[PDB]
Amino acid sequence: GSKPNYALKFTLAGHTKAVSSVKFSPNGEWLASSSADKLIKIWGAYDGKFEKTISGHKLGISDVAWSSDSNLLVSASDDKTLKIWDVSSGKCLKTLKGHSNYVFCCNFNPQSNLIVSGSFDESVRIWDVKTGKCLKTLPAHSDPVSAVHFNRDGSLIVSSSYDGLCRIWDTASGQCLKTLIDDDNPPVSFVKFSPNGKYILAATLDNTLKLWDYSKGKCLKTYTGHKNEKYCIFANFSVTGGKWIVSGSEDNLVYIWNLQTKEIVQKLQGHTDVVISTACHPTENIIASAALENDKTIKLWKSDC
Ligand SMILES: COC(=O)NCCCCc1ncc(CO)[nH]1
Image (cartoon, rainbow, N blue to C red; front, side, top):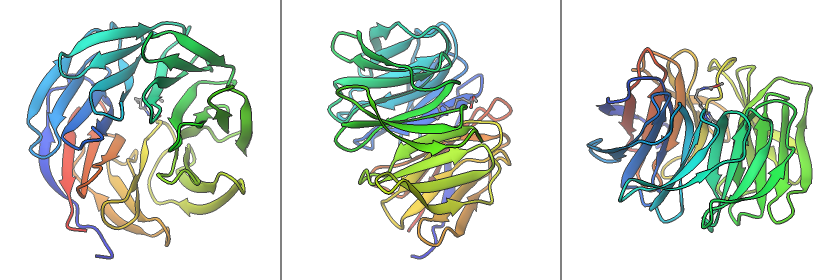
């Protein structure tokens, strides 16, 4: 259909502080959640059945990411570390030390041999997953790094920052290929590549989402209507039904846009605080949405389209 009809299926509770992110396992069976409560909780994507807690970080966690094979997780913490976890045993495999301030964002490359991290120390770091050692430190930005993402073949890294810049990096050399957004500001609160790796989705703290052509360096689409002036809110490409942009908002709603028409096609109501994080299931029309400390719940939504 030409509009989704996402409806609340489950409300997942357990976190005792603000939830920071939610990500579906690539294999679709797990939802992972991180929180300011220093915990990672694993949930069944289809029944929301609480699976396990993963503990070890000494301070709050801002991001969590899956390896390609759904077996490993990596988390970014205010304790200035990342931890690589084995999901099955729930054990810390490695602790990545090097950042001199909070680690805000992380992702595996598709090969899942590397992890990219963004920090308040204004650097992007590339880590070897096998040895937990830092391979490279990029003096990426002049303010905290809000987001990092590898493209589909893992040859580029896109990073965003409160310095109002979005930069793309050559993984192998760590040299800057392009400075996509060269504004004094507003703060770039989030960036990721599109699934084909042609486009960058970029959020700015003037309630604006923009789809960029990486090669051309030009803004293709603008999405508006939501509120985003304070928080680094994740945005997603929904690709299992109709082609949507998904994002949280500071008005406690999940916003869904038609990618092409830039039209608002649904607003999800239920959260009682800022929706900080959203995730689109890899195979089913299901959304995970996560909220800050007044709510602390994860909501699973299902659509027919
Ligand atoms: C400005 O600080 C926050 O927004 N705190 C909320 C928790 C962190 C949410 C987040 N972590 C990573 C991203 C985007 O890469 N967004």
